[PDB]
Amino acid sequence: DKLIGSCVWGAVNYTSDCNGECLLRGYKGGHCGSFANVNCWCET
């Protein structure tokens, strides 16, 4: 997996646009943790 940042509306390294932060890295459509809604990861 290829982390990107956090996925909490009120935290540091805030993402806001997972797919965005992932696209920024040329990664594939990322998403937010499935069983840990807090950090986002890419679908690599």
Image: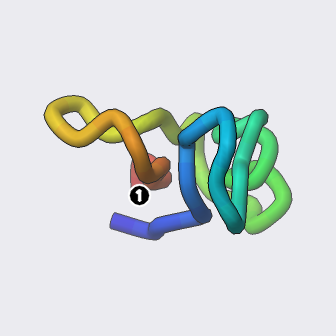
Q: In this view, does 36 lie above or below 4?
A: above
- In this rendering, would 37 be left or right of 28? left
- In this rendering, would 27 be left or right of 17? left
Q: Which colour scheme is used?
A: rainbow
- In the image shown, does 18 or 13 lie closer to the viewer? 13
Q: In which quarter of the image is residue 6?
A: bottom right
Residue 16 point in image, percent of width and height: 76, 36
- In the image shown, does 37 or 34 lie closer to the viewer? 37
Residue 18 point in image, percent of width and height: 65, 40
Dot 1: element: loop
Q: Is residue 6 above or below residue 19?
A: below
The residue drawn where x is 56% and y is 40% is: 8
The residue drawn where x is 64% and y is 54% is: 11
- Which quadrant holds the N terminus? bottom left
- In this rendering, would 33 be left or right of 6? left
Q: How crowded is mark 1: few (under 14 residues within 10 Å), some or many (20 or more)?
A: few
Q: Mark 1 points at which residue?
A: 44
Q: Quadrant of residue 44?
A: bottom left
The residue drawn where x is 32% and y is 39% is: 33
Residue 13 point in image, percent of width and height: 70, 66
- In the image shown, does 21 or 23 lie closer to the viewer? 21
Q: How many marks?
A: 1
Specify the amino acid type for callout 1: Thr
Q: Is residue 18 above or below residue 14?
A: above
Residue 19 point in image, percent of width and height: 68, 37
Q: In this view, does 44 lie above or below 16?
A: below
- In the image shown, does 19 or 16 lie closer to the viewer? 16
The residue drawn where x is 67% and y is 43% is: 10
